[PDB]
Image (cartoon, rainbow over all chains, first blue to last red; front, side):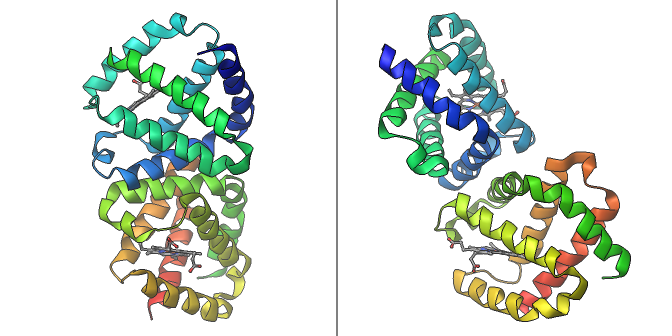
Length: 131
Length: 131
Ligand code: HEM
Ligand code: HEM
């Protein structure tokens, strides 16, 4: 993750953040449509789950200049995900759905370059969570 | 619906409307989780579908004093729904999911009385769409 990618993440978060409630919920609607077998894993209210997911994305943006500082947080999260029935092959599916949902909601407000940067950041977060 | 119910629809819409995008999207997430097979009927972007659904709810509120006047509009909507592959048994499922999603997003901000009014209004709308 180079300086340019870090900037694109900070810059695009300024448009994601004000829209984060909708983006998170759109993500879950899209996920449950696209991957009908993962919805059974979610046991708590989706409204609160969406808030939790977007909160963590904001933490990734806040720590984007030093992600290594987030390895422990992410390792704990990955551990809980195993307890939720999540498996390694879920991560690419969730990543694609999240990025596509941001793209859908923001349209021309979200560049291909920003999409690529978020893809790398997601890939990193997922690698840390799956060890 | 009676006068008190009309007033409840109008007053509770003041809380639903500013949150209508989120409620719509939560509704689709909840619907797709409750009945995963139903998602195949939805071919267009969920973000735009949620907007359209909540637009019609706003029309129901706008016309709440004279629902009779919306019968043609609802009949046309019901006709298009038949084309989508929607059938009678879908209606209770969707109503339950919609009401529960409004309740979930607003919590105690959605009063028992308002929820009872909206339940009746949904039933009337469904009845007209399927007559
Ligand atoms: C970088 C990727 C991801 C992030 C940042 C993330 C974030 C979160 C957060 C913050 C929570 C709240 C609970 C907790 O903190 O332990 C959560 C719960 C959950 N996540 Fe993820 N997640 C990711 C990937 C995934 C994947 C790939 C799946 C696969 C389906 C998934 C499914 C779930 C489930 C089932 C729960 C528990 C829901 C419940 O409370 O019942 N997540 N996730
Ligand atoms: C009062 C109840 C309902 C309302 C107000 C409503 C509203 C709408 C609206 C405004 C649209 C946009 C397209 C159009 O105007 O024809 C739509 C599309 C659609 N609705 Fe409904 N609807 C209701 C019930 C249902 C039910 C019970 C189902 C069962 C699954 C359903 C499934 C669909 C589908 C599959 C589409 C098309 C999606 C697409 O274009 O890909 N709706 N609905």
